[PDB]
Length: 52
Length: 51
Image 1 (cartoon, rainbow over the protein chains, first blue to last red):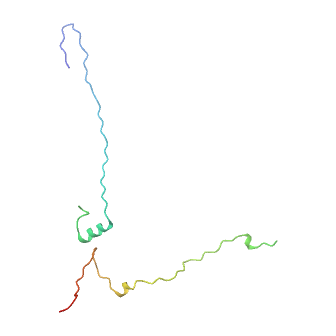
Image 2: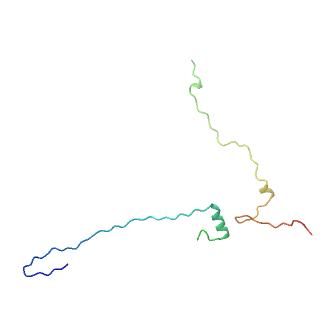
Image 3: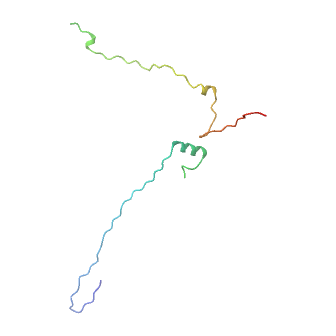
């Protein structure tokens, strides 16, 4: 902040202040399990279940 | 006494290949032709009694 002063008034000390901030790191996974038969049923009948 | 070969304990000679008893193959694969199929249970229609 600025200040107003007379011709010999004492000038004050005033400074910016700073802080750091840090990210976190978040690891995400999705796993889906199915029987070998679901691959055969899907790719024979063209179900589109695996693509879904 | 005299030097016998039993003192050396010589290794036996391996002979190549394997001896096997035979195994019978599938009879159903010889007696019934395989039809083409798609994965899953088939269904067949049968006459049970005539008029």
